[PDB]
Image (cartoon, rainbow, N blue to C red; front, side):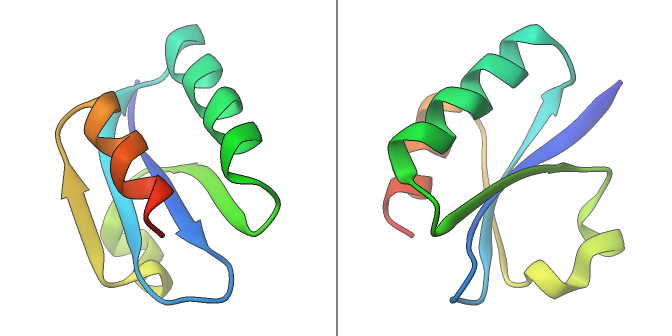
Length: 74
């Protein structure tokens, strides 16, 4: 199924979001990025932004590479 993968700093408002297919590729990508960014950053999959208004404002990106760049700037 489809989801959004989300990166968010626990102590700051807003997030980075990428629409993505659930699967092993996404799980590996998210696991690797979680290691690089550390414990202060949350990486989570959600169904859709309106179900998670607490992560606003959303910055949407269109590739894994752009997601990694923007997540690292949080």
